[PDB]
Image (cartoon, rainbow, N blue to C red; front, side, top):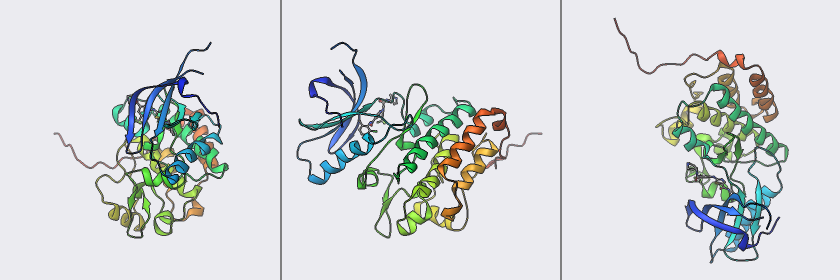
Length: 291
Ligand SMILES: Cc1cccc(Cl)c1NC(=O)c1cnc(Nc2cc(C(=O)NC3CCNCC3)cc(C(F)(F)F)c2)s1
């Protein structure tokens, strides 16, 4: 892992914060070249052994990856305190908030392109034998080219740190509305449970960041899923896209597409973009009648 001297890092603005460090936007000097914008996460003094292992472990995992749709690591400060992880800077931030702040501003083809990128990053991770466990729009980052990159890596720290992941009756901490039934029921997290999550992300993207299952409680979500109910079609959603998200939500893990199948289908739809003009029917909640 590239070790960066602290004199090369200028933290400029807090963009996220937690009890044991912050995330900053800043600049990285890498004498001749212009400084480059970066994101910087810190780990403050007094950290425990487990915190150090988890913090640097995220950097270690990220350093094993080289893919357009996976956040790129610039390096770490580990020889000086506070320790830091430095990555590329994603100008548009988290995908969930981005979509909610840009409601209706993109074309269907742009939205599907975002899903293609996410799927390519997930195919890469699954092929690398990395199970994400927390795939959700809140853990995707977006740059000024609209490229979506998978974020949030690690072992126990991922679900521990995400406030959407809640303690269950069985004792595990999981983000219920994004998690496959086998992962909820018996702690079985695999690339196929990540495919379930990806289907939820597809729904998030096509609804501009609606909250999955709206106000249903976590218990009610699990009950509906076990009863066979599934999220309904977003408004303005290509039929092929809704069909694909439905396949991701098969109860039987073995029936779900693999990420390779998802990427292939999304590629083909984008290459023949008229295919996206055929929309799934939308079930209205409200009737407007006028004579
Ligand atoms: C530094 C680091 C360590 C370990 C793992 C990772 Cl993935 C990282 N890298 C990062 O966290 C980030 C890389 N790019 C980021 N861009 C970003 C940018 C912003 C943000 O300041 N700007 C945009 C400008 C204001 N409009 C909305 C978003 C906000 C966030 C969020 F709130 F989410 F934190 C993120 S965060």
